[PDB]
Image 1 (cartoon, rainbow, N blue to C red):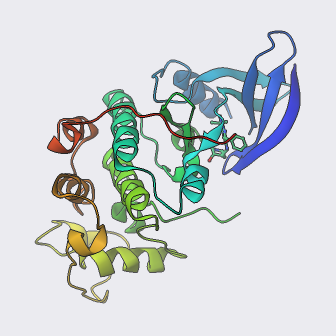
Image 2 (image 1 turned 45 degrees about the vertical axis):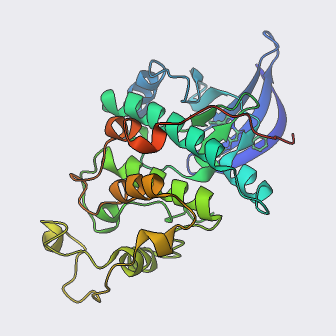
Length: 278
Ligand SMILES: CC(C)c1cnn2c(NCc3ccccc3)cc(NC[C@@H]3CCNC[C@H]3O)nc12
């Protein structure tokens, strides 16, 4: 029912093609991937928001799974690699952050988490919109990147909360601003140790219950924190204050997406259009 145009990427969950529906003329992203997955995925069809890549259809046929998504022309990694010499301008960074926080406040209010936010999962159009892609696919179901993984996941917490998406988004914010990934780990311990080196080794004072976590070891080295002004210059004081609340160790103290939308950093938010080369 779909004509493959080109290979657009390769996810955890299978390979993705830009495709054309032969009956409608519609251009879509076709992703080819147990009764349990079916019901979860079908619940995603109703989870609709302008800052979430629209799931158009779930095609369970000939004992196979295809997800048909809205197509967007560009991802945030490629826009960042392409914006490398001058950086993404601040008003655009802020507008993308604000829109992503809208999409997360939406999903989280419906008790749906992403779990794997990353620049390659954040898709942009020519209208200045940014959208979350693959929402809900990790709960429904190449080396997987760890750079955006929240410390409670890395510490083996089995029951992650919406706080894990705020951490990832925090990491992406820092990266848009500095033009470098914040925590580029290449293994779980390297990832954890890069977080500790920047934010301090967490203890019982900043994160109660931490030393009881499954993969916590008393033997972790103990590094002191660094100042956000060393970590993300040239971000201003409001952006630094928001980021630090998005990067709180304790997931219970981490700001929510809805509180983050009220933060003074967003007082002058606007919706710029990007210069996009397609
Ligand atoms: C949510 C999906 C299925 C969708 C809709 N548009 N789009 C684009 N568009 C950006 C793009 C366009 C042309 C060439 C490369 C990338 C890229 C893309 N890449 C797939 C990766 C692997 C699976 N999960 C999402 C992403 O990490 N997935 C999607």
